Amino acid sequence: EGAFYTREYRNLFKEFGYSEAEIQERVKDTWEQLFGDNPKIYYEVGDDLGYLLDTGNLDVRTEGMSYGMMMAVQMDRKDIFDRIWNWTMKNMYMTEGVHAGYFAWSCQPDGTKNSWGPAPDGEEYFALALFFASHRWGDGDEQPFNYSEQARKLLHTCVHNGEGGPGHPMWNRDNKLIKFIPEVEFSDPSYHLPHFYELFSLWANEEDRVFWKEAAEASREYLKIACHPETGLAPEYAYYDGTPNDEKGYGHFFSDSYRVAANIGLDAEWFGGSEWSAEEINKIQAFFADKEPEDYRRYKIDGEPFEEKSLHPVGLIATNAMGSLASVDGPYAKANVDLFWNTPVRTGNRRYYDNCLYLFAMLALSGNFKIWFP
Ligand code: NI
Image (cartoon, rainbow, N blue to C red; front, side):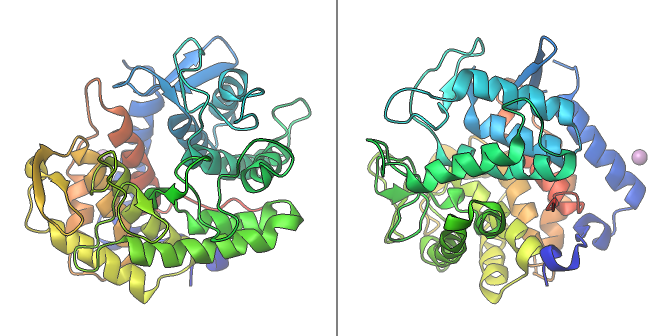
């Protein structure tokens, strides 16, 4: 049974032989490298602002801001959480345009919006992080620090947008699947977080609780058809029918895709393992068992390699290791966790994406990526 029920989180590092002391030290060190003052992906501005910088693209993305908020609440750092959320509401929240009610996906460090289009994976992380913040610290008096209200309001928009305006929802109401973006009719496998939706089914506005339960089930079934049956690899973008959408080159196993294994691992830990999840993780790990990180490439989902190397091999390592939570007795589970332990956080101008995935894996594998209840 999952941690949602037992309230006990598996410390896979410990179960695989690592000492509690070294695990504690490693988790803290990872956090400090990313959020400490050492030019690191988190930047503090003034006394009430802060943001996570996509060091490589020189911009601030809702993906990173929502990740940062989730990391901060997991680490019990309300000061950091509030700085990020404040920046988000001040510079990213849109009050005008067809996407009013959503958050501009990319902004410049000075706050200027680079687009008025949102990224659904950001919104869903914002919502859960806000629910967790409300549960750990309580809703603040002054907005936008009234966390739970912000979360319910946002999820209301995600489901009902368009009913009273020219906007569109982030979930298709008929198939209950999250969309790549509001105005298209296809998805992105890595955006599916059934474990998040299970919680939304308990904390969102009551009128949408049944919907969220259906979304969780829909996403679990979708992942089954989106992942290649032999390799377990999922495409970055996929049509609702499950097949890859390669219209613009996103139909292969690349950057976005890496998160699928991590998501499957966390869902298994929180809500329980499953035969499909264990088998899926075994497939992915088996595929990479005879491949060296330095040689990781972009692959068609059937395994065929491209000449192009993975742009985020450290992130791939981290996600494959996090996936072990869904197959603790898998033939390659231990090897993946060991590989991750022996892989330092990424350095350089493009440390951002890899390191976000890295910290999430460090938290999950150590039993510190928890559900915070009311
Ligand atoms: Ni030590």
